[PDB]
Image (spheres, helix red, strand yellow):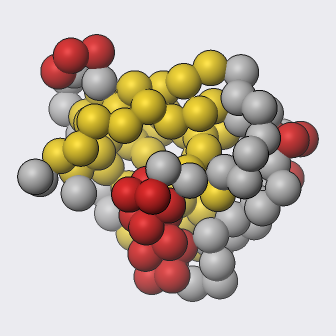
Amino acid sequence: KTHVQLSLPVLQVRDVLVRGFGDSVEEVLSEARQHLKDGTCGLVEVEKGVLPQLEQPYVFIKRSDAAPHGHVMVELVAELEGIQYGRSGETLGVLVPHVGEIPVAYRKVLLRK
C-alpha cells in the first residue's frame, strides 16, 4: 500500500534515550522508515529548546494534505545544517527511535510509504 495507518507514541524530549537515527540525510530517512515499519518509532512535538536537545540530521513528519479515519496524511523531510531534503506542509513533530520510553499521547498518521 502507498499509505500505512500508524499510531506514533509521543515522547517528552528529556526522556528520549536515542536522540536521532544516524549521521547522514540518507541514513536518517532510511532508518526512520525502517522504525516506522517495525513499530519502533516515536514522535517529539517541536517547541522552543527541543531541536538543540536532539541529534542532526533531523527527520520531521510534515502534513502532506488537508485526514482519513482520524489519521493525518504525512511525509518525511530530513534537515541538516538548515537545509531540508523534501518539501511538505506543517511539522507534526520530529521522529526518534522508540526504545520503551513511556509516551504522553499518540499521534494517528497515514504515512506516505
Quadrant in the picture for residue 105: top right
Choose between 36 and 50: the one closer to the eye: 36
The image shows residue 30 at horizontal and vertical percentages of 43, 75
Locate residue 93: give its quadrant: top right
Quadrant the C terminus occupies: bottom left
Q: Could you tell me how many numbered marks the image carries? A: 0
Q: Is residue 84 left or right of residue 18?
A: left
Q: Is residue 14 above or below residue 78?
A: above
Above-or-below relation of 10 to 101: above
Q: Is residue 41 left or right of residue 47?
A: left
Identify the residue shown where x is 72% and y is 53%.
99
**Picture quadrant of residue 67:** top left
Measuring from the top left, give residue 27's x and y in whole percent: 51, 81
* Residue with the most extreme right position: 14
The answer to whether residue 101 is above or below residue 78 is above
x and y, in percent, of residue 47 in the image: 72, 32
Nearer to the camera, 99 or 63: 99
Q: Which residue is depicted at the point 64% across and 78% down?
A: 22
Above or below for 104 versus 34: above
Q: Can I make out residue 77 in this image? A: no
For the question of whether residue 107 can be seen, the reply is yes
At x 64% / y 57%, what residue is drawn? 97
Q: Who is closer to the viewer here, 51 or 27?
A: 27
Residue at image position (74%, 45%) is 100
Q: Position of residue 10 (x, y in %)?
A: 63, 31
Q: Quick one: which residue is furthest to the left in this view? A: 1
